[PDB]
Amino acid sequence: GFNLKVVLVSFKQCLDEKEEVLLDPYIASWKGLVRFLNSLGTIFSFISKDVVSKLRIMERLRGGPQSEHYRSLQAMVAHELSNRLVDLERRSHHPESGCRTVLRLHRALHWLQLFLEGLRTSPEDARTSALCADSYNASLAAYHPWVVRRAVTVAFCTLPTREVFLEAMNVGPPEQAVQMLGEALPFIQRVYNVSQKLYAEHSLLDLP
Ligand SMILES: CCCCCCCCCCCCC/C=C/[C@@H](O)[C@H](COP(=O)(O)O)NC(=O)CCCCCCCCCCC
Image (cartoon, rainbow, N blue to C red; front, side):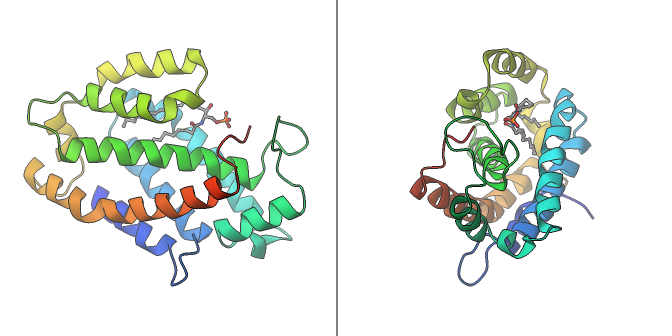
């Protein structure tokens, strides 16, 4: 019943007719990713908590007195910039602003998209560990302190084989998994592109 396709396709729900990035569905989709990650039984389950803690921050903003301004990422950015609830230069009175919090998930989404795309078009003899590192170095690595970068990089060598990873998506044999990624990744890509435009245009790509 539960599989990676269900999660990827849930990202369709994150964009409305005006391509507002809706926060509730975004959270729901990320909870799907966490459940998938935890199902893989790798050492990276050690880091699921960081995602979960970030989702809870966002859920608490959605449960608060300004909940309506957190309905979409676009609304969130407008509200937090106009009320100075985002630390722009250095961490200060708003260490857990919606803007800086969502940024971390967004960067991770970028990594995930690069990793899954890499996997989708990889040769049969490609190593999962290499797909992960190359995509990590492309993306998330620059935002992590050296101690984290080095530990993550080493941990990559302990990942399952390409075949096992594809089968773990639970959508059939590797060949079916590969076609699934092609049909489903565009949903996560669209969410990423719209979110990246939002952050880029507001010069928020480097929030502390
Ligand atoms: C299945 C193999 C998964 C490979 C995942 C490779 C990337 C792992 C990154 C681990 C980062 C170390 C944990 C804590 C990092 C935090 O410092 C940063 C910055 O947050 P801040 O401290 O400023 O609040 N947090 C992040 O970069 C977000 C956590 C990354 C989530 C990884 C996505 C895994 C989802 C997999 C779903 C298939």
